[PDB]
């Protein structure tokens, strides 16, 4: 597998053998990096005694394909000096924002290339034909396929901290954001071109008439672009999206994209009846609000050996109510697995759980009816599970139907789906079943928020029968 | 319907806001039925009494004392209810106690009831434990008022221990009182829930006074109190420190986390302070350990006051050291002398020989009484406060050279600790006399005897 | 020792070869126990890499009896001692070597047997430190899914070991301590196969197993300030370099050629040569 990452291929116009390094085929790691550097050492060994040139195919080079700093430091020492001095040219194809940030992070190691004439950045695919013949070009077929059948939308603007003029090329497997203005990479003014393959485009959002948002997998920051034809770009990316997940497949969890699960594991254990658990959970929540950059009312710190009071309930509530108002984007998974932790906890902790989850329940109204059916089905799963905990916990019943169901009925526009959940969960039990009876009882506590809408909906759904 | 909970609450919150003249009978009645109801029905009870608590403020303080002690009876019955219900405990702390402390001007009677309730329980009882626990949820409504009342109340008791002095301070009559209310500060010290931005010099004074005292749990609690004090001092946003001060506080937290300070605070065998602090024959105290701890807290406190203009932390802190430094009380006299030696930035001419007066009087009691070891220890402390204070002394008095003969007379005694204390006194005396350059003019064997010649007979 | 394998990995199991193995275990332990008098010639030739696979494949067939269980225990200390001296030794490849030790030890770790349990689990802890799991037989299946299944295979084994532990005091405390270090090791080693199976530990019935596991979830969270360490902890300013001569007089000569590298690598970067 390492033979296709780096291989001898072709002879340039200047009479030098060309070595192709495909960066996207490399995966970062110990034995992969060691096999890579040994393959480069074996393949380069007949030819670094002569002048040679290297094509670096940096298409789709991301965090999976980086060199670690200890490994990147090896590339400047393990080869002889004439191996570096015999490099006539380095053709760097498809530099992107990740590669630019990588070289900015490693300006000390790559100072031998900074300002070098030997680096020829291939900002346009026809420029590589200025030094290598087309029959001598042996770039991978995927790299050539990324250049074909591109639906190009020029004069777009990628909005960021620095808004950059770009052109968006949408092909049947990928989206290429090519910078229309030069930026500094290794001291050279080049045209960047970010490449996003099929497996990365998660969410396709049309914000307004001249802005859209593209979401990249394992990348927290969304991409936003401004263009005259944003709706055409949106429908084309939805078309190729529908093309690849309905053709190629006919649950992989990263440590980053589970904030709600870790937050609930912190908060439920923060009020626990043991000082060691309570001490460690505080440091975990402090680290969790340090990494993901979400607002707290007060500052935090991580220190071992704190002494934390046996109750934390007002502090815990003052935290879990502040996040729900400050950022609502993570209510779903938090509320999903919070109920499970409620279900397998002791009763004294069970009293804490509803007490600190009741502010998070107030803002799933926006996550209903927002035209994405998967999250709207997830809401129905949550409400069914709320029905299950209302059935199963007979003992705590006035408190739960005072807390969460009245808060549900207080807000408008959620009334339909709670009534459909009531009807389809009433139908399963049958008349005389407890499942129908006590949930019909909770309908009263639901109705006290808004009288007219619940009355009209119950009477209308009855009269249609 | 089978529930009426929103209806019952919507009734019960209407009358409480509407007419307050019948709150007392209702609150007295409702707690008894709360005590003899089924648990799911009991969940309704606080849910509908919580509006009735908020208008109890106008009944207190309105100068009818029978109703005022009825308010006390109601509060104590709520205490009994708070203790009894462990399964329902987060709910009763969330609902009634935070709502109780959230309204100002009820706080004095509630704290008073707390302290008299915890006094009957005693230290190590369940009652004072859960009561110090409940004080945390109390204090969040008004941080500064609860903090100031707790600190001032405890400061008065340490002040009034001087009336009937006992040397140990574990022997004094209100030792259990100080221990019980120190547990309050341990519980309440978490997230600047006692205001460190205004009560810092009072707080370090109590910290200095009660290191390494009592059983193992309180000894670890003092350490955890110090850690939480520095942590909340770091995380406080009202002070708006510079970066370097925050850096040195962040290093100071790791400094106090070290096992060396575990040895200084008396917790040597125990790995974790927080484990032993929450679980519910003593090794002797070393006074130089108190000197090191006071120097560390001095460094922290000076680094904090560098940013704050005219903070006057040191002024109150030196007065609170000095007042205990110049009385009789053997539990509090040596520690206050060492603290006044370490902190002070100013010395009076009569003050240094009043320290000498303290030495002379203390040497008599150990002479006529071969009964108390502590009568020696004060003299040792009276040495130590000399050594820090002499460089601060002004233009050349005969006391500069008289302290050499003082050090020699201390060295003439055969006790180990007095010898070790006198050696440091003689070292700093030689170094300060060398820095003031008297020794350039004369040999040591003439300038010291110049003072000895008028006093040659004794 | 390679003579002992008859045909296609058929082990002979003679008493003379077993006695020779019992000798060579103590020989390898006493050789690897020394840390001084020149470690540059400890490199060898395919160091102990072929050795240990042959050794474990001999001793696994030896069975369950007192001398056999004793030789098994001695091998369990030997693996740990060898794993201590990793930086001295030199394999051509060690990842699938390590995985084969884990496979050939975990299969038979589970009155002196319970002594062997904490004799061997420590060796598993030492082996698992920083080891990326990989399928040795990666053919026939996708490698990452097989990695996740292998993580579940080793992870449920430590789960039902800890559960058997949780049901006399000091050896059970030793199990309940040593198992969660193994947990922390294979979770911190690789996370992309780890987290989706391992996040259910946060609600465990044993509280003490939670926080330390949950401690690991802190560290990973900042897996992805040393300049002051290079400043005041490394230079030791305002003096005639006291900590420098301290580390000169303390560090042994065998790492001096390393040490002579690491001092001047710093100070020419800070211009105090």
Image (spheres, rainbow, N blue to C red):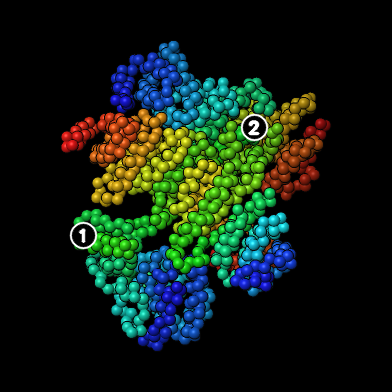
Mark 1 crowd level (few <14, some 14–19, many ≥20, 10 Å Cα): some
Residue extending farthest left: A464
Tell me which residue sits at (48%, 51%) in the image. C198
Q: Secondary structure at mark 2?
A: loop
Disc 1: which residue = A231
Q: Which mark is residue B178?
A: none
Q: Nearer the viewer, residue B131 or B60?
A: B131
Asked whether the viewer can see residue A79, the reply is yes
Quarter that holds the N terminus of chain A: bottom left
Tell me which residue sits at (31%, 62%) in the image. A250
Tell me which residue sits at (28%, 30%) in the image. A444
Q: Nearer the viewer, residue C108 or A276?
A: C108
Q: Chain of mark 1?
A: A
Q: Nearer the viewer, residue C24 or A7?
A: C24
Disc 2: which residue = B215
Q: Is residue B365 left or right of residue B111?
A: right
Q: Tell whether label 1 touches label 2 (CB within 8 Å).
A: no
The percent coordinates of residue B180 (x first, y second) are: 57, 27
Mark 2 crowd level (few <14, some 14–19, many ≥20, 10 Å Cα): few
Q: Is residue A82 left or right of residue B43?
A: right
Whether A388 is drawn above or below A111: the answer is above
The percent coordinates of residue A458 (x first, y second) are: 21, 34
Q: Chain of mark 2?
A: B
Tell me which residue sits at (34%, 32%) in the image. A434
């Amino acid at each position: 597998k390492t033979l296709s990452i780096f291989y001898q291929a072709g002879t340039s116009k200047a009479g030098n053998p060309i070595f192709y390094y495909v960066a996207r085929r490399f995966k970062t790691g110990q034995i992969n990096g060691d096999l890579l550097i040994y393959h480069v050492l074996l393949t380069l060994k007949p030819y670094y005694a002569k002048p040679y040139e290297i094509v670096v195919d940096l298409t789709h080079t991301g965090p999976s394909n980086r060199f670690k700093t200890d490994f990147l430091s090896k590339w400047f020492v393990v080869f002889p000096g004439f191996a570096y001095d015999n490099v006539s040219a380095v053709y760097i194809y498809n530099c992107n924002s990740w590669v630019r940030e990588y070289t900015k992070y490693h300006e000390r190691l790559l100072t031998g290339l900074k300002g070098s004439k030997r680096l020829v950045f291939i900002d346009c695919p026809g420029k590589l034909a200025e030094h290598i013949e087309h029959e001598q070009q042996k770039l991978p077929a995927a790299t050539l396929a990324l250049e074909e059948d591109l639906k190009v939308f020029h004069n777009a603007l990628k909005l960021a901290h620095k808004d950059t003029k770009v052109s968006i090329k949408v092909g049947s497997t990928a989206v290429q954001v090519t910078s229309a203005e030069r930026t500094k990479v290794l001291g050279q003014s080049v045209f960047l071109n970010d490449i996003y393959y099929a497996s990365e485009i998660e969410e396709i959002c049309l914000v307004d008439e001249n802005q859209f948002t593209l979401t990249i997998a394992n990348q927290g920051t969304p991409l936003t672009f401004m263009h005259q034809e944003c709706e055409a770009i949106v429908q084309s990316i939805i078309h190729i999206r529908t093309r690849w997940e309905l053709s190629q497949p006919d649950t992989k969890i990263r440590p980053k994209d589970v904030p709600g699960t870790l937050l609930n594991i912190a908060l439920l254990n923060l009020g626990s009846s043991d000082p060691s658990l309570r001490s460690a959970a505080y440091n975990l929540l402090c680290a969790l609000t340090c990494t993901f950059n979400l607002k707290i009312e007060g500052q935090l710190l991580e220190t071992s050996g704190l002494c934390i009071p046996a109750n934390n309930t007002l502090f815990i509530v003052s935290i879990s109510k502040t996040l729900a108002a400050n950022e609502p984007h993570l209510t779903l998974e938090f509320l999903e697995e919070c109920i499970s932790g409620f279900s397998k906890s002791s009763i004294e902790l069970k009293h804490l759980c509803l007490e600190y989850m009741t502010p998070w329940l107030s803002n799933l109204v926006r996550f209903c009816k927002h035209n994405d059916d998967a999250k709207r089905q997830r809401v129905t799963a949550i409400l069914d599970k709320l029905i299950t905990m209302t059935i199963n916990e007979k003992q705590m019943y006035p408190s739960i139907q005072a807390k969460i169901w009245g808060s549900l009925g207080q807000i408008t526009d959620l009334l339909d789906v709670v009534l459909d959940s009531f009807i389809k969960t009433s139908a399963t039990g049958g008349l005389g079943s407890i499942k129908a009876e006590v949930m019909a009882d909770t309908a009263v506590a639901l109705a006290s928020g808004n009288v007219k809408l619940v009355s009209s909906k119950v009477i209308g759904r009855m009269c249609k029968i | 319907p089978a529930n009426n909970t929103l209806f019952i609450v919507s009734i019960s919150k209407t009358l409480a806001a509407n007419e307050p003249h019948l709150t007392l009978e209702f609150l007295e009645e409702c707690i008894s039925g709360f005590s003899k109801s089924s648990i799911e029905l009991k969940h309704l009870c606080l849910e509908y009494m919580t509006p009735w608590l908020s208008n109890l403020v106008r009944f207190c303080k309105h100068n009818d004392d029978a109703k005022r002690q009825r308010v006390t009876a109601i509060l104590d019955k709520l205490i009994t209810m708070t203790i009894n219900e462990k399964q329902m405990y987060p709910s009763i702390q969330a609902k009634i106690w935070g709502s109780l402390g959230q309204i100002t001007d009820l706080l004095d009677v509630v704290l008073d009831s707390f302290i008299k309730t915890s006094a009957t329980g005693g230290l190590g009882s369940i009652k004072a434990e859960v009561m110090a626990d409940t004080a945390v949820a109390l204090a969040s409504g008004n941080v500064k008022l609860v903090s100031s009342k707790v600190i001032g109340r405890m400061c008065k008791i340490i002040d009034k221990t001087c009336l009937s002095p006992t040397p140990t301070l574990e022997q004094h009559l209100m030792w259990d009182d100080i221990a019980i209310l120190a547990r309050y500060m341990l519980m309440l010290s978490f997230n600047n829930s006692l205001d460190v931005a205004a009560h810092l010099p009072y707080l370090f004074h109590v910290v200095t006074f009660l290191v390494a005292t009592g059983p193992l749990s309180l000894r670890a609690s003092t350490h955890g109190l110090v850690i939480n004090i520095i942590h909340s001092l770091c995380t406080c946003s009202q002070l708006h420190f510079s970066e370097e001060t925050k850096q040195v506080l962040r290093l100071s937290l790791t400094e106090f986390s070290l096992p060396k300070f575990y040895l200084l605070f008396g917790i040597s065998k125990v790995k974790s302070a927080a484990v032993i602090a929450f679980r519910s024959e003593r090794e002797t105290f070393a006074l130089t350990s108190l000197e090191t701890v006071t120097e560390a807290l001095l460094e922290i406190m000076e680094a904090c006051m560098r940013d704050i203009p005219t903070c006057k932390w040191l002024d109150q802190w030196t007065e609170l050291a000095q007042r205990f430094a110049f009385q009789y009380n053997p539990s509090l006299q040596p520690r206050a002398l060492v603290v006044f030696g370490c902190i002070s930035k100013r010395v009076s001419h009569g003050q240094i020989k009043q320290i000498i007066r303290i030495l002379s009087k203390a040497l008599e009691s150990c002479l006529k009484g071969p009964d108390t070891y502590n009568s020696q220890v004060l003299i040792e402390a009276t040495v130590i406060a000399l050594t820090k204070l002499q460089p601060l002394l002004n233009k050349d008095s005969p006391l500069h050279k008289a302290l050499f003969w003082v050090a020699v007379a201390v060295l003439q005694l055969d006790e180990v600790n007095l010898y070790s204390a006198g050696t440091a006194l003689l070292e700093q005396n030689l170094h300060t006399l060398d820095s003031l350059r008297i020794f350039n003019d004369k040999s040591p064997e003439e300038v010291f005897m110049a003072i000895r010649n008028p006093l040659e007979w004794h | 020792i390679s003579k002992f394998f008859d045909s296609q990995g058929q082990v002979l199991l003679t008493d003379t070869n077993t006695q020779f193995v019992e000798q060579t275990i103590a020989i390898m332990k006493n050789l690897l126990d020394n840390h001084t008098e020149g470690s540059s010639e400890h490199l060898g030739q395919a160091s102990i890499e072929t050795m240990m696979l042959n050794l474990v494949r001999y001793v696994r067939v030896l069975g369950n009896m007192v001398h056999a269980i004793q030789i098994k225990t001695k091998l369990c200390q030997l693996v740990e001692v060898m794993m201590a001296r990793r930086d001295d030794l030199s394999f051509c490849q060690e990842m699938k070597f390590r995985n084969k030790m884990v496979e050939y030890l975990t299969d038979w770790v589970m009155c002196l047997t319970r002594d062997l349990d904490q004799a061997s689990m420590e060796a598993v802890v030492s082996l698992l430190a920083g080891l990326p799991l990989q399928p040795e037989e990666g053919d026939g299946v996708e490698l990452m899914e097989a990695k996740s299944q292998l993580f579940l295979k080793y992870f449920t084994l430590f789960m039902n070991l800890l559960n058997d532990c949780s049901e006399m005091s000091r050896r059970l405390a030793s199990l309940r301590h040593c198992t969660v270090l193994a947990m922390s090791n294979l979770l911190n080693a690789n996370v992309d196969s780890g987290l989706m199976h391992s996040i259910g530990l946060g609600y465990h019935k044993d509280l003490q197993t939670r926080a330390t596991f949950m401690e690991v979830l802190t560290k990973i969270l900042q897996q992805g300030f040393e300049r002051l360490v290079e400043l005041v902890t490394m230079m030791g300013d305002q003096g005639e370099l006291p900590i420098a001569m301290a580390l000169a007089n303390v560090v042994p000569c065998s790492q001096w050629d390393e040490l002579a590298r690491v001092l001047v690598t710093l100070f020419d970067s800070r211009h105090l040569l």
